[PDB]
Image (cartoon, rainbow, N blue to C red; front, side, top):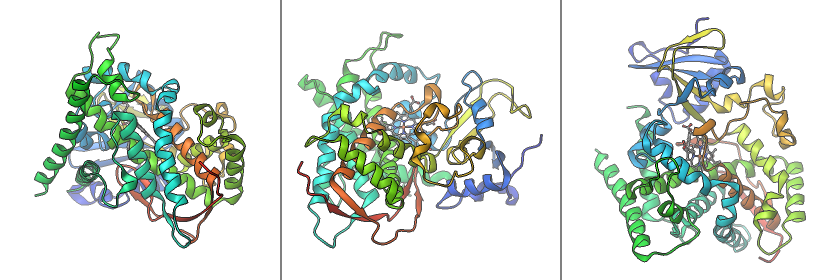
Length: 444
Ligand code: HEM
Ligand SMILES: NCCc1ccc(O)c(O)c1
C-alpha cells in the first residue's frame, strides 16, 4: 500500500506543520484524519508516524528496529552528552551505563531512595497546609518543584530548595532555558547563552562529583552507585564526564515527565469526584502512619491505576523514534529499507479503539484492574524494550507516594472550572491548572 501524507508547503514539504506551540496535538489530529500510519517529510528527511497497536507491535520488535535519535534525544544531546537518554544503543557508554544503573533503578532500590522522596513530599504537603484561606495552588508549578528537588536529592544528594524560592536555583534556570533552546530548533545570537547555561550545569555537577570523591562519603544516592559500580561485561566503571552526563540526564529528562504525570492525574481526579473519592478512600485506608512507608506505597493499587490511566490519556513523554536495522516490510503492506525511520505517536496508540474499546476518551482507571488483559505493546508510556525508561519505577513510586499523601491530607476544589490547556515543551503538561485545597488536618 501507498502511505497517506498530510498537507504540503511547496519546497518545505510537511515541515511548517511543526511550526506551532502544540506540535504533538497537531500530529494527533492528523492521525485522526489519515489513520494508523502517515509519511511526514521535511527538507532532507522522512519519517513515518505510527498510531495503531497493529503497527507499533512490529516497530517494537527489537530484532527489527532500534532507538533512533531524532527530536527529544538529538537536540537534548547538546546538554546530556552520551548519557543514557541521548546515546545510540551501539555507543559503548550506553551499554556500560545501562548495566551499571539498572540495579539502582529497580523496585528494590526504591526502598533506598524512599526517605529522600518522603523528605520532599513532606515539604510539598507542609507548603499546602500553610496556605491561607483564599489562596490557591499552581499545580504543575508545585509538581515541578517537587520532582526536580526529589531527583536532585536521590540523584546526587544536592538540595535545590525549590520550595524556598520564587526564582529557581541557577542550575534549574540554566537547564530549563537550555531545554527550551534545544526544543525551539524543531523549526528555524543566544548561542552564547546556551553555552553559558551548559557551563553552569557542568560546573555544578563536576563540582559535586569532585567533592564526593574528595570526601569519600557514602550515601543513598545514584552518584554513590555510579562512583562504586563496575559494568559486569566490560569490567569498567563510568568515567567522571559520563557520570555528570547521567546526573544532568536524570534531571533534564526525568523531572518534567514526572511533574506532568502528577499534574494530569490531579486534573483527572478533580474532574471525576467519584474516582477522586475512591482514591482518597484508598489513601486513608492504607497510609495509616505519620509518613508513608515504601511498603504502604506498594499497597496503593487504585492510586497506581489512576496514574496509569492519566498516562494512557496524556503520556507526558509523548513520542519516540526508531530506525529499521535491516530492509523489512511493516504491517504486511509497507516495505522499508534499512535506516528508514518511524515515530511512535503514544497518545494516539493509547486511543486505539481496537485495543481499548470505544470509550478511549473517558477517564476510567478501572481499565487497569487487570493489566494482563492489555494486548502486547498497546500501552507504552515508558517507551520500549532495552531502551525503555530506566526511571519508570522511580517515576511511579514518586507519583504514587505523592498523590497518595495529597489525597490523604487534603480535599480538592476545581475552583475556576479549569479548561484543559496542554503546553508542550519536551513533555506535556496542563498549563495554568490551579486548585484549592482544604486540609483534612491530619498531622504529619
Ligand atoms: C512519568 C514520567 C516518565 C515518563 C512518561 C518517561 C518516559 C520515557 C520514555 C518514553 C522513554 C523512551 C525515550 C526514547 O525511546 O527515545 C524514556 C527513557 C528514559 N528515561 Fe524516562 N520517563 C519518565 C520519568 C523518568 C525519570 C524520573 C527518570 C530518572 C532517571 C527518567 C530517565 C530516563 C532515561 C535515563 C531514559 C533512557 C533509558 C535508556 O535508553 O537507556 N525518566 N522515558
Ligand atoms: N524520560 C523521559 C524523556 C522523554 C521526554 C520526551 C519524549 O518525547 C521522550 O520520548 C522521552
